[PDB]
Image (cartoon, coloured by chain):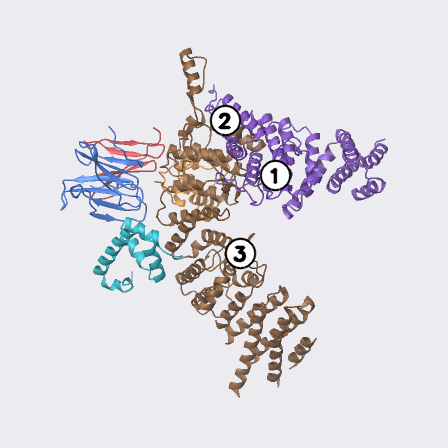
Chain colours: A purple, B red, C brown, D orange, E blue, F cyan
Amino acid sequence: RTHDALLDQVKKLDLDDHPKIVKNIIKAYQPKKEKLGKFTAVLLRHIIFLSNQNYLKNVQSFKRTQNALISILKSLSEKYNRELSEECRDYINEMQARYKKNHFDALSNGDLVFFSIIGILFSTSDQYHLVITPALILMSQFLEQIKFNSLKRIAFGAVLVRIVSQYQRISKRYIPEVVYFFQKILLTFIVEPLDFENIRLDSYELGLPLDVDFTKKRSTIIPLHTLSTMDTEAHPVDQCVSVLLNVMESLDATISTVWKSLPAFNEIILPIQQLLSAYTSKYSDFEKPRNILNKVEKLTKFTEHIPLALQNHKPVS
Amino acid sequence: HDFAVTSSTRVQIFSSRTRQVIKTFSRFKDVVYSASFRSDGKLLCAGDATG
Amino acid sequence: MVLLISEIKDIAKKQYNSIIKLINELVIPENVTQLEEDETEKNLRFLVMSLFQIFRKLFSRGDLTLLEKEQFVNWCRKVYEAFKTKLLAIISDIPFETSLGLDSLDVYLQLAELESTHFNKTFRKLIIALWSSNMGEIEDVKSSGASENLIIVEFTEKYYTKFADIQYYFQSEFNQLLEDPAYQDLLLKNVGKWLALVNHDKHCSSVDADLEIFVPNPPQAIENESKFKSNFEKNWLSLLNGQLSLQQYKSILLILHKRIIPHFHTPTKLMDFLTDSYNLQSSNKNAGVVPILALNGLFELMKRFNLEYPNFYMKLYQIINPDLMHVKYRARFFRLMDVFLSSTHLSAHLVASFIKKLARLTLESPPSAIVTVIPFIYNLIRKHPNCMIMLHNPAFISNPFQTPDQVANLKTLKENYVDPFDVHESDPELTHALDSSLWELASLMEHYHPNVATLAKIFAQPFKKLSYNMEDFLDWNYDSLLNAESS
Amino acid sequence: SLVVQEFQHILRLLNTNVDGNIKIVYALTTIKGVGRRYSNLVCKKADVDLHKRAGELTQEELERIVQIMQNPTHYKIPAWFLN
Amino acid sequence: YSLNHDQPVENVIAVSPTQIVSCGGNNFKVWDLTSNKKLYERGNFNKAVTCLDYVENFDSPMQSALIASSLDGHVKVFDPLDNFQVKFGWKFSGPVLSCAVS
Amino acid sequence: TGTVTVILSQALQSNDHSLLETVLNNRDERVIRDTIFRLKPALAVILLERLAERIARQTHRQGPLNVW
């Protein structure tokens, strides 16, 4: 309770399966200010640590207790926000200390799940926030400055794209960085080239050959990041097409939520349009890309595509 | 015996034997752009940056 | 140990014979350091440092104090043996022995002072030793810098940046040593050593500050600044002709742009080098960014003297790319953009081409690059108000107070409208960017960051001012933005 | 066919905002606290042409003006002239 | 009718009642109106030509002279009677913007 | 490498006597060979004509100019 390490040791000694139960009992005893703020600090640190350490238990024995912990966090966040924001700021500062010390060697699926829970909990629709907007630009920097050269980084980008898709389905904003991420991922997947050299990718080793069945039984998004990101070094074409379809589905969801309202979706998608046309000319059996092209063509037909009226203001009296 | 030169908000008339600033024009607001004499050698016209 | 006992004996002291024996022991310390290459006396080298201090004290005593020909020959031989032992310890210090290198450098400097006061060849031998020295982490530091040495970097940072006379004789002896064939190849191998020795920005030709004198009697080291320029230019032409790599290439481009120009005397040879650099366009993604500083040098070259580069704005249109956004020199490149596009003979076609290229760039560009490009766009539009039609067409806007015939005509015009801008067209004058509006600036309106969105609202609102302070709104980064937001 | 050159609008000077579209002596007069021949002779001592507009006078002679006027006694300014 | 000077023309000078000069960009084309076509063209200039004037029937060994300044202090004197052949030149360090003759 | 090809070509396209003098002041044979290798044929021809007229004007200048 008083110390994060001490309370983590107590929870581990009691049980990893019912650390949520032990912490809930302790918090109920305590609520019955500073004590509960320290409990919130230790609970956030402990759930991040658990996400970093272990996910071997299945949905029926680990996801249930994780969701119980999430509910306890919802209760303590509905009861307290100031201490939670302060520890969020500290957690930031330590993230960027880690990142400046090691650009890629000091990140965590714990940071990713922290971002996800922050987005789920807070009123993400706010234009400016002491927590959301800082973490928003931190997430942008995370997805942009990472030297994309491996499938674990690709999956990190994919989960970041999913969380910002939630962000801009509840907020409806636009990210040129996620556009660049999509273009870079497509180019590094189909590098195997002559039509795209301004994207400046990093890795010349991974591609996409014509040995995929792309069926429904073929591995879907099914994101087990706490396992996929650490077993992704073994690289089958099934895993490659699964992550490709994951990023493509997130791209389509972002389109259908915000980018239809985006006025320049046509010129946003033009590089993606060329990449997907190359996809179709190379494979000729990609139904989801076909539907994406149909949707973009529909948007081009329905958009005004007319010169704007930016400098049209009313006269002064 | 004389010629006109444009400059910053300033039109200068110089002589030939003296080659000195003979006449000064500074009633412009912004920099002048063009200067031209008439065939009769009396009127000089200047195009400025005010239109 | 034995070194300390010899030190005590020499301090207490046949005094010439004892000093000769101590000098022989300090020359045997070259073999001690050779064995130290495998293990520096259990990786401590404390005895070696004590022996070096003893040798320095003995050399000082010998310089203070000293068959006259035989005695002078013996004293000079002992002093030269100590200096050569220090030079060999510095040269063969493949292992990173910081204390041993520092002791060797201090002993060599003291011996050089004593020789200059009582006895140039010692200087060239010292430089030969320092350049024959090589370390694994020192050879071609690729992430940053030129050569992450130890001995030559400390030599520069506490010995070269202080004495202008030593700088003058320094460059003269490099000219001599480069005329020397084998050591010319030595410099060719250790190019980055000179880069690390020269990027320190406090050289003699920098008349902004003054450098104090090492030798009590400087032998006419202020004979000619143009002679200093000639030595600088000869050394630099030799090094740029020999053994160039990518990181050293970028570093020499930076030092040329910022520091060499005050120190160089063959600007036409710099012209040829810089135009080769700017026309250097290959498939290397790492070598495709040199044209930035290459054009920086070329343009300051054009300013210093009036020469040409054909299809200049053609090359700018070609060179503008998102790789510029991804590289970290885009701040200086935007200063360059200011000083090019500030001309008064540019046209609507050129400004429209550049603004549309930058609009696609800000459609796909990082937010720091967005806040760098916003002031440029605003100032460019304000300077050339001819692009108000593409900012908002007056024919495409509607009004209730006009006839249904014109309503139908406007509807048909909107139906038959098409965007005619061409991206692949390398001619800024030929790209029909006048008709193309900025849906990309509309997306910038619909950005996500609050500060960027406010800058977008500034774009949308009518242009009331001219001064936008490009410098203050020019250098921004992710970390800087986070610091500002937290503050 | 690019050409290079070397003008300023309303600009700040000693926390006072004065236009670049007015003659130099009288811009310095409208600088608060100082007056007619104060401005005239500070221009004279700064050694600039008196027929110019404040769009001219780039920053180095601008700062000579500032330093001379803010150190008047150190430039042989007579006490009976001082305020 | 129009006669094409592809690069941006910055000067048009009616040198003669039948001939004109288009002075723009690096080169300059001397056209004739009656033939509606360029009699000659000279591209002997270094950068874009910035100014061009003409003088005729004055006290000189050469009857007519054509001056052109091309942004280098580089002023060059040609002559229409010699098909605008190089006759003289001066170079002034500052890039000249205008030139003229009495 | 250290050639002066672009300056030679510019001077020959616009025959600036001062610039051509400053660029012929040099005497490095490797640079001479590199220039004339990366020089245009007709431009080098008119360059040779310029060298001829300068040797005629100042035969004292022809010393290092005898190898151009």
Q: Which residue is mark 2?
A: C461
Q: Output the chain of dot 3.
A: C
In the rendered view, would you say C78 is above or below E42? Answer: below
How crowded pointer 3 is (Cα within 10 Å; few <14, some 14-19, many 20+) is rated as many
Q: Disc 3 or 2, which lies upstream in sequence? A: 3
Residue identifier under label 1: A143
The kind of residue tagged 1 is: Leu
Count the marks: how many?
A: 3
Asked if badges 3 and 1 are on one and the same chain, I answer: no
Residue C200: percent from left, percent from top: 52, 57
Which quadrant is the N terminus of chain D positioned in? top left
Task: Give the number of the mark in front: 2 or 1.
Answer: 1
CA gap, disc 2 and disc 1: 32 Å
- Mark nearer the viewer, 3 or 1: 1
The answer for how far apart the CA atoms under marks 3 and 2 are is: 48 Å
For disc 3, the marked residue is C146
Residue contact between numbered discs 3 and 1, judged by CB atoms under 8 Å: no
Q: Chain of mark 1?
A: A
Which quadrant of the structure image shows residue C239?
Answer: bottom left
Q: Quadrant of residue B40?
A: top left
C352 vs C116, left or right, is: left
The type of residue carrying mark 3 is Ala
Circle 1 — which element?
Answer: helix
| Amino acid, disc 2 | Gln
Residue shown at the point (38%, 52%) measured from the top left: C271
